Each structure stands twice: as C-alpha cells, then as structure tokens.
Image (cartoon, rainbow, N blue to C red):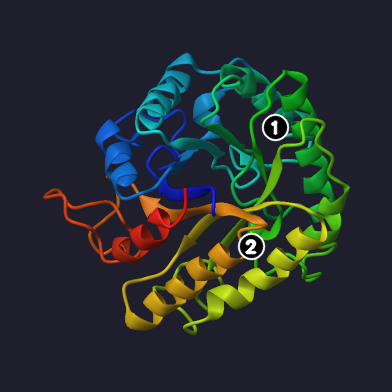
Amino acid sequence: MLKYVGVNLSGAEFNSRKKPGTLFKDYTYPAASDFSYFAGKGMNTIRLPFLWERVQPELNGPLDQAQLGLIKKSLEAAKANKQYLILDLHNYATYSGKRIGTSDVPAGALADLWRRLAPEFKDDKAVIFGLMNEPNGISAPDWANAAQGTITAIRKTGAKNLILVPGTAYTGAHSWRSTSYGVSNAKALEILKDPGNNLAFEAHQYLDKDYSGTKPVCTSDSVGQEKLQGFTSWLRENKQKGFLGEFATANNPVCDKALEGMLTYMEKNSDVWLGWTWWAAGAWWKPDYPFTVQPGKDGSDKPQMAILSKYARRAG
C-alpha cells in the first residue's frame, strides 16, 4: 500500500562546476532502456536530478529549450513504462555557488524557476515537482518562507501536481526535530499552506555515522527505522505525507538487514509515507561505487536490487 517506489537516475547533475557544460561529456540523461529495466523490476517511480544552471542559464531568465527537451524526452520514457517522474532541482539551495536568500540569489528567483517550469508539465499526471535537493546553510524559517513563495507561484500557474517540499540541514530525516541548526524543520514547516492541497515532505536518510553516505557502512542493523521515527511521528501528528527521496546501503550482511528493516518500516507506516527512491542508478557510476543499482552491460542485477525488487513489487 505504498504509492511510489523507485530509483534516482543520476547523470544530468554531474560536474556542477561546468556551466553550461557539454552533453555526453560533462553530464548525461538516461537511456529509455534504463526506464524500462527498472519498470521491469517493479519500480514505478524515477527521481530525475538536473541542474538549475542548465535549465535556466540566467537567473529570472527564460528556460533553455534544449535542456527542457531532454527532460521531456525522459518523461516520454517514463510514461511509456507507466512510471512517475520526479523533477529534482539538484542544487543544494545554491545557484552558481551562491545561496538562496542572499542578494545575489533572492527567494523569488527560485519562485521564478518553478513559475516557468510548472506549466510545461501541468497536465501530466506522471510529473511530481521536487523543489530543491538538500537545502543547507539557510535557516529553517528562511527556507520554509522560500518554499512557501515557490508553492504559491506553482499553484498560481494552474499546476495541480504533487509538490515535494524539503527542509534545511540537507533535509535529513534524523535531524527533523533537532534544534542544533536553529529553529527545527518540524517547527518551521508547520506554517506551510498549499491552495492546491497536494503536498508532501521530502526527507533523505543515510546510515553511516554522520548520515551523509560517504562511508559504505551501516552503524547497526536497525538504524534506518530509528532515524525515520521523529519524521514519521511528525507527519502523523500534522496529517501530512512523506517521501524518502534519497537513501542507500552498501552490499554487506549488516547493511542488508538494515535495508530490510527500513523498507518494512515504510510499508507498516504507509499511512504517512508515500514511498521512496533509491540513490542511485545511471550509466556514469564507477565499478567500485557502493550504492549503484544500475545493471551491468550484460544486464545482470546489482546485489542490493534483489532486496529492492522484493519491496517494490509489494507496493503499487
């Protein structure tokens, strides 16, 4: 009874340094056959990272027609495979290195981006709007405010699509109630109003000591379940819905158990969780990269795909 299950198809957000960058050299979009492979593994949802700098080359300026065309090409692959596509603005609350909220990048500039992007997808039932990947270094109240302005902007254009709203502090599920970074995401995001009434809160969760995914280690076989509880609790209290936009475990016995506990957790908490997308797949991950579920050239599954498919087919 979970609605959305799938993967991040990573590639378009690579080498963020190179603006605008060259297609096939600095970044890539996924092949139609990738969409097909994951749909065959029972996954109905693709999160698609792309760069703000690539889609809108000038702040408040018109959209790049070529980059928009590549996004639309990915959508037709998703639609054919009966999949949902999350448009993920993979930008860490920055545009060309400068934070949202500064006089270089005002809050209304993010609102302008989505004001332009939304009506391009307003009919498509397969398109979900992911406002910003992992905001950080901006206070929770200030970020919440920028999220609100963006939401208002999207709904003004007539778009009724699901909006995925992140918090600050890298939108970690573990730290949702914490006051270590100031006013919590929990307290700051209470104020949010959506006139379209189609909102969910995007959280990310990794299982190493510092919850970043820089180490291929899970700290215990149950750490996933424990770190989601504050957020799940919050969603239930507030009659809100949640999404696990990014999460990953390495290929080892302890990590495999932790992944199973986590996916079982979201299944029994499906009253508030709308679903999850794994980090990651895409043709540009190295062989030794611990989190890849991109199939080999021969077409064989990566080790974690076995567990992922089991739970993917349990949903829909």
| Identity, as a three-letter code, of the amino acid under mark 1 | Leu
Crowding around mark 1 (Cα neighbors within 10 Å: few <14, some 14 to 19, many 20+) is many
Q: Secondary structure at mark 1?
A: helix
* Residue found at x 30% / y 52%: 285
Residue 102 in sight from this viewpoint: no
Residue 241 vs residue 115, the one in the foreground: 241
Q: Position of residue 211 (x, y in %)?
A: 55, 70
Answer whether labels 2 and 1 touch (C-beta < 8 Å).
no
* Quarter occupied by residue 170: bottom right
* Quarter occupied by residue 31: top left
Residue 69 vs residue 100, the one in the foreground: 69
| Identity, as a three-letter code, of the amino acid under mark 2 | Gly
Q: Is residue 145 above or below residue 311?
A: above
Q: Which residue lies under the disc numbered 1?
A: 110
Q: Position of residue 115 (x, y in %)?
A: 69, 22
Q: Position of residue 190 (x, y in %)?
A: 85, 52
* Residue found at x 62% / y 64%: 269
Left or right side of 62 for 99: right
Could you tell me how far apart the alpha carbons at marks 2 and 1 are, in whole angstroms?
A: 21 Å
Q: Which residue lies under the disc numbered 2?
A: 172
Left or right side of 293 for 17: right
Mark positioned earlier in the residue sequence (2 or 1): 1
Q: Is residue 50 above or below residue 206?
A: above
Residue 148 vs residue 7, the one in the foreground: 7
User: Considering the image in quadrants, where does the N terminus appear?
Assistant: bottom right
Left or right side of 21 for 246: right
Left or right side of 287 for 67: right
